[PDB]
Amino acid sequence: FSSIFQRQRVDALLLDLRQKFPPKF
Amino acid sequence: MYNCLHSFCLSLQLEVLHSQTLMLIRERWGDLVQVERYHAGKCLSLSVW
Image 1 (spheres, rainbow over the protein chains, first blue to last red):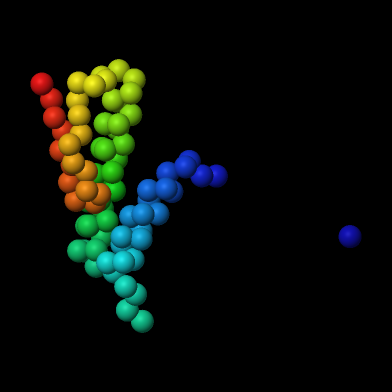
Image 2: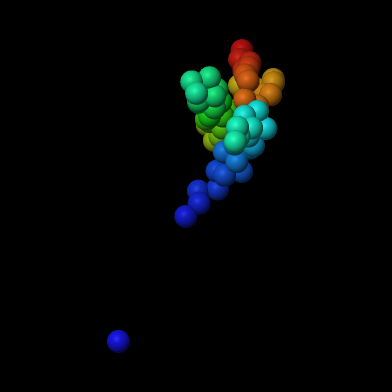
């Protein structure tokens, strides 16, 4: 009846982005 | 919206270049070009001759 092992950098940029741009809700 | 995107945008490009320089320093060019400062997300500087 996959990851090309570059998230060890792009992740940092996102953190730098989040740390600099908090959500407004 | 434009300010936030432009920044992130202008930061991923900078990283692309630093990676390339380091990779080149190994294979072909080698100990003839040097990095002197890389604070991430803002700027880098290279030395030659």
